[PDB]
Image: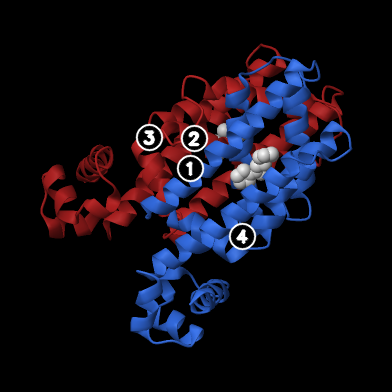
Chain colours: A red, B blue
Amino acid sequence: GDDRELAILATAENLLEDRPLADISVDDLAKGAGISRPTFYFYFPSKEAVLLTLLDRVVNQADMALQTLAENPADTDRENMWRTGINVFFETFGSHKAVTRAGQAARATSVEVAELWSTFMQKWIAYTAAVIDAERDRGAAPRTLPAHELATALNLMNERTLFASFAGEQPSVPEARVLDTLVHIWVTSIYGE
Amino acid sequence: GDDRELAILATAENLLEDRPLADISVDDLAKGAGISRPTFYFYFPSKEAVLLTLLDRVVNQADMALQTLAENPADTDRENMWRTGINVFFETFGSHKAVTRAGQAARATSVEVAELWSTFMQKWIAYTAAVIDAERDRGAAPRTLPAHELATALNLMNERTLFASFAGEQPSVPEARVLDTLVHIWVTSIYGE
Ligand SMILES: O=C(NC[C@@H]1CCOC1)N1CCCC1
Ligand SMILES: O=C(NC[C@@H]1CCOC1)N1CCCC1
């Protein structure tokens, strides 16, 4: 039951490492999961819904990891605290590059994937502004830009920069340099007067 | 000749303000330009090539404006110099929102649009790193991150942030705040130790 479902999700993730969603048929997903086509439709309405679930799981795994961090402050300086938080997204999306890339391309065409991404980005930007506000309240960061607008651009930068790096786009920051790069932009823009 | 061509480009830009490229037919472009369908095919191989030309013109207009600025230093402080440079992209792409949005969505599917965007982004990132390097050489900015990687993330941030603002995406920086927002990120990340 949940096993036939996981089989179908695991096949689509393995297949997405090789071709885009358009070059993958329901029969490919069925065959790979060891089931027939009509049995597939019992678990998912379409291959698009398969992607939606995969992205849902990846986005929830990132969100849960960040919530864990939030309730368990790392005992370290400010720069390292932002690094560990950004690293949650670098490791989680960077461990699922194929879903990340397919999820990103599906935003243009799927309302559900567009709204999932948007809900979570709003949540992650609100958390980022809450932390900047705490930092200003404590006297550790200066009152420069509106925190929420600062948070928005910094989260958009990470979405675009992480994802260009993972896809190996031309241009992009190499993946072994993107964490340092982004932490520097964050710390100087949050703390710089 | 060049007039029938401009008519077709002007119709596609006006139509793209209302629906996406998929909801626009060659007959719509022809009718709007006052020509037949076979006459259309004489000037463009497809409606996709129409978009490619429109984006080409917008990208070249931005690049030319920036080159003008480069050969005509504005007599002002560092923050205002970055502001005027980013403003070239805010005004040029912000005066062509429909083409910008359609050009962006076409990157997923059109190799030509993907390579146009990439060539120009490489050029704009190289210029940005050349300027950061000049700034460090003169003793005005500290030697922090590799300039070219810094330039890459800052240009990716602007592409994503400008474009979310222009499309009114949820989340996005409001369009009357995005220039200030980005200049602050740039100046603190370039000059901050
Ligand atoms: O790096 C990111 N954000 C890291 C921020 C730092 C702490 O919470 C969010 N993101 C947000 C969407 C894709 C990548
Ligand atoms: O804001 C941008 N760049 C501004 C930089 C500042 C000076 O030259 C480039 N971009 C680059 C692509 C889309 C928007």
- Marks 3 and 2: in contact by CB < 8 Å? no
State the mark number for residue A185. none
Residue B149 seen: yes
Q: Do labels 3 and 1 share a chain?
A: no
Query: Can you name the residue that lies furthest to the top here?
Result: A76
Q: Mark 1 points at which residue?
A: B118
Residue under label 2? A171
Work out whether disc 2 and disc 3 sit on a shared chain: yes
Q: Whole-Å distance between the Cαs marked 1 and 2?
A: 7 Å
Quadrant in the picture for residue B192:
top right
Left or right of B6, for residue A152: right
Residue A159 visible to the viewer: no
Q: How far apart are marks 3 and 4 (CA)?
A: 26 Å
- Residue B57, located in which quarter of the rendered image? bottom right
Q: Identify residue type, mark 1.
A: Ser
Within 10 Å of the Cα at label 1, are there few (<14), some (14-19), or many (20+) other Cα atoms? some
| Location of residue B131 in the rendering, given as x and y in whole percent from the top left corner | 70, 29
Marks 3 & 4, CB-CB < 8 Å contact = no
Ligand 1 under 8 Å from disc 3 Cβ: no
Task: Give the quadrant of the C terminus of chain A.
Answer: top right
Q: Residue at x 13, y 57 (%)?
A: A37
Q: In this view, does B31 lie to the left or right of B97?
A: left
Q: Do the residues labelled 1 and 2 touch (CB within 8 Å)?
A: yes
Say above or below: B63 vs A177. Answer: below
User: Is A85 left or right of B49, judged from the image as shown?
Assistant: right
What crowding class fits label 3: few (fewer than 14 Cα within 10 Å), some (14-19), or many (20 or more)? Answer: some
What amino acid is at disc 4?
Answer: Ala
Does the CB distance between marks 3 and 1 fall below 8 Å?
Answer: no
Question: Front-most of B85 and A191?
Answer: B85
Please tell me in which quarter of the rendered image ligand 2 is found.
Answer: top right
Residue pointed to by mark 4? B167
User: Which amino acid lies under the numbered mark 2 shown in the image of this protein?
Assistant: Pro
